[PDB]
Image (cartoon, rainbow over all chains, first blue to last red; front, side, top):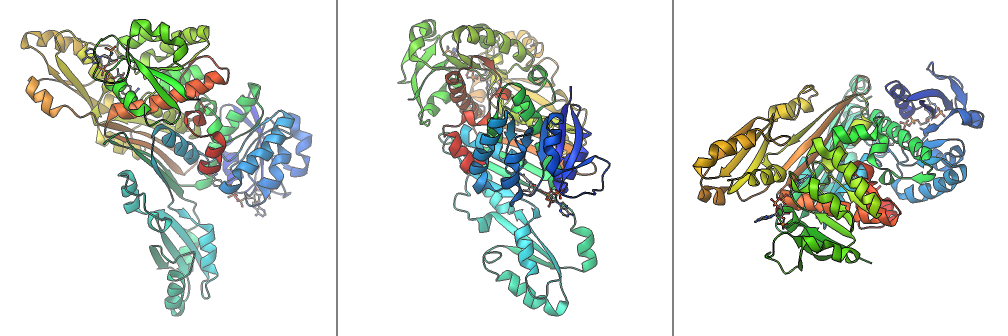
Length: 319
Length: 319
Ligand SMILES: NC(=O)c1ccc[n+]([C@@H]2O[C@H](COP(=O)([O-])OP(=O)(O)OC[C@H]3O[C@@H](n4cnc5c(N)ncnc54)[C@H](OP(=O)(O)O)[C@@H]3O)[C@@H](O)[C@H]2O)c1
Ligand SMILES: NC(=O)c1ccc[n+]([C@@H]2O[C@H](COP(=O)([O-])OP(=O)(O)OC[C@H]3O[C@@H](n4cnc5c(N)ncnc54)[C@H](OP(=O)(O)O)[C@@H]3O)[C@@H](O)[C@H]2O)c1
């Protein structure tokens, strides 16, 4: 029978997860658990406080709350009721998050997949594979083009800025050096460039630009494009969530170079993140069905467990 | 303690494995098992008929005989004595090979990793991940331009062939269509061509050309160009072994496109194939130590098992 899934948290990721369940042959969406009473959806909405009343009805909880504080504090509680899958992206906290989720999931006999998505997630998997295969490798991850929320907020704090967004993009020159094994000395200020889009009165532009180009820690030292655009233009063309990146790994085998490159081009960040999250939710359920329990990163899941196809079918068609 | 490894077969792949074991922090090369008495190496060379007398001294056997004929009949015998790792590349025969290897490895309590390399191997893994994540997807694989080790070994076993290599060349138009999501229907056979370069007495050309064009799995049904050249021409222009390829997956999440691309650029095909085979060798030994036995494709191995580093270190650094 189908895996019974529910969504905790109805933001962008939760909405992406919801709409993609319809594309799954083997999953049924039971409901959304939200801290808000009224959501613009026909999916049943339940109080997050009542997850315990649906625990027997839910095989996998997709955790779609914010990573900043909500995941660390809430996720261990949810693991007592189902398998859980999160996209927790605070890399420096992932070992602790895994340990705490492992205690809770083990005690409950469930499987928690932590830190799925694309980074952490697919990029994590590609970093490890390429580094494992290529002895004495060089490796770089590049992000974007995508919105930087920290750098965007830094732009708005500039006196005179009415609206603003900042994007980070890979430097094409640094990408090409990485492909050739010659990026070893590049700093973060040389691997990426930045694009600013700012709404501001023209009388303030000279000051705002100099504020931007000499703002420390956020913009000093980077290649920065500064675009002053109209509020009408801003509200209409910068509401999307494009993202992606590259993982490039090289290694030498005695006078011979090898280049591994993994590229993602995403029109909608939470749509791809949800796609990854859903696949690892299938994995988590199957792992529990096999008798496993505890918490796992994407490094600990064999690839076939993500697929809705039978393993024998994958072997005959895709290997 | 280090994994004790040995190499069966001393062609291009076997030589690549040999030179790369020195790079591994956790492997020692015990020797080479060969059908030939005289190899140009200081590594201990043993008779392949005597592998049974080394069974307690060898944890992992790297199987580096030819795929076209040697692997199917010979590989299952070696699973009696150690974990094995092969790069068997006859996709239409991989389910059968896995099944017979699984019986042999299970009886012996060893782990057989079958069909490693880059295709099968890394490309198989990338096909499965991208197809599992992108629910509605288009996916195509492209190979080359470059020298194919399996096809080349197959040519050299044809009676009357003195020297031979095969190249595969992808349609760059089809690759561009794939990126735009417009290739959909095209197969590998429809988007590649094969070039053979063969040194043979002219009296043997008719028979050799027929053995090429009617060779199942490797050449039957492909667009194949056959070149009969002189030995001097071969020896100067056909020594390099570069290759590479692309796995391209596109998908839509409801009005938003995503592209996943995996790219290899290999200066020396057998060096990277060996790099992959070695990593899966590490994995097979570790799986055996965890209590597993039988035969597994690359789809069935958790990524962290390939790495020489501790899982905790990979999580903290790479996820
Ligand atoms: N690993 C990766 O590759 C990757 C990539 C992208 C994102 N992520 C993670 O995904 C997480 C969530 O992304 P998101 O874009 O979904 O964040 P979000 O849109 O801010 O949703 C976060 C939470 O805010 C609440 N919320 C949503 N709309 C609200 C409103 N109008 N008023 C009040 N509360 C509201 C929801 O909880 P209730 O329904 O309970 O209110 C939702 O769970 C991020 O924190 C990020 O770490 C991971
Ligand atoms: N899966 C992948 O991605 C991938 C990519 C590349 C290659 N491969 C596989 O790798 C396999 C090996 O490629 P290869 O280039 O190593 O094949 P090879 O160079 O033709 O040598 C293959 C076997 O022939 C024997 N041999 C070598 N030199 C010989 C000589 N001068 N006279 C007689 N016998 C000789 C060796 O066994 P003895 O020492 O016992 O004679 C060796 O094991 C290919 O068959 C291919 O299927 C896989």
